[PDB]
Amino acid sequence: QGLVYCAEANPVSFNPQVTTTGSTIDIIANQLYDRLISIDPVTAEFKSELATDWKISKDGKSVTFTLRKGVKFHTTAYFTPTREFNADDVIFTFSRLFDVYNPYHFVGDANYPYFQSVGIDQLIRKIVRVSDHQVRFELFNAESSFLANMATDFAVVLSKEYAMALKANNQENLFDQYPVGTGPYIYKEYRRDHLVRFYKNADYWKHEVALEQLVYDITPNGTTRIAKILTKECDVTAHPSSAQLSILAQRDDINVERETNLNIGYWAFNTERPPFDNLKVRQALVHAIDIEKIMQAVYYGNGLRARSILPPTSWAFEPQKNMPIFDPQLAKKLLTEAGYEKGFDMSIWAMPVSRIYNPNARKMAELMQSDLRKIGVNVNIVEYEWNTFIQRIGEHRHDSVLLGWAADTPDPDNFFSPLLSCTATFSGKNPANWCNPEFDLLLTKALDTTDLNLRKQYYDAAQSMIIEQLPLYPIAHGMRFQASSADVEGITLGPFGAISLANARKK
Image (cartoon, rainbow, N blue to C red; front, top):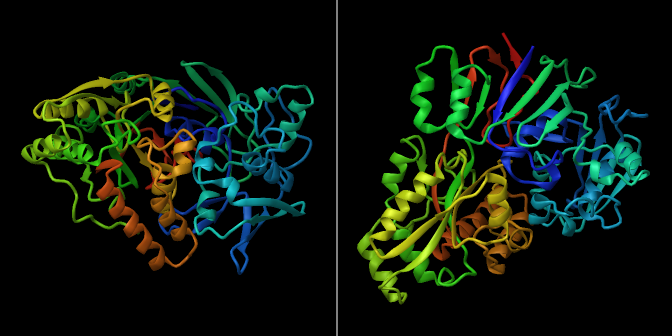
């Protein structure tokens, strides 16, 4: 038997290294690949994946991974391995991110958005082959988030042999399109904007894989995904429309999981674009927004109002005393002092698809447009296809944007570096377009130490800084939902990271 998953977007690649977009990661990361290590969703301890063991040196500058033996790369229509997984695959995979001499470093777009945002090339000096099944990472400095970064869905292990065979024929451009991994499923077919089809990996190292066939039905329209699960054309539906949760709840043969999750939905200002570079304007705009109306009409009472950019479940969470409160009069008063008592036009870019942190950006934008009109700010709503949308926000084309972040790890840095740091801005991320070295300094110091208390102190000051300067306005944290036919079991919906179907089964 097989399983049909209704995906909300086309995958932008079959290599997790080149995107941070959940829509893509959900499809490819846990299905085709494995990592060196993962993070236990309950205890937050690192768990063995392709690494059986790891040790950090005294000074935190060397990390040694012992590797699993007997691990096979996929046999696909286009590739048949000659050897089992080893240290060379690790050294190739990760050096491709930071080493300009790696022959794939510049392949495709030459962009690795997560890794560049956390400044990977200022972190890894080199990777040493101590033996066939052991490698040592040498770092320029200790970073307390390093293992957490090696546990992200982006840190998959690629095939050096495949990479090299394609290079010998000048077909490096196929590497990221026709993937080879060690994961539970294998690439069979992809039809742009229609479907992707994976097959069971009969050689999977970790366990026997239950499903023979995995199909992703690319279906951007939220109501259509509801429709498809109701008619049983799909067995699993990504990100169900909150307006249709009640309908799904009433169907006996449909299960809907609802889980707490580390995420933030926010309204980011393009801080390099006047007038949004003016702090008074940013303050004015936020006080104009009826957030409680939003908690009700958008999140349907299922979200938690944001008290900080960090979700209350983050270990560094600290509620901010000066969170802006809804006050149109105060909003009007600031707008004037900012020099805009006749207001101005502005765009609010809205996502076309439901996300954990914002189930309906369009509706939220419309509510905001209505609120803002009341103080003379004329909003036009901008919206594009999901992947196009992410790309243009990455180019900072917008005045302001409704976006957010679903955390890939429970390490608080995962909210800060990829979101608000200088390097993030220079790597096509950071919707606020905010480069503040004094803020970046706090994040560096939080990483110079492993001491939780010391880290939290810096994250406390980082949190306060975001509220004072308002590069973005934290709005809410959402629940993670997923709908599936009652015939489906073994699906993992955790508090961070992408979906996995590795243990999925029917009946």
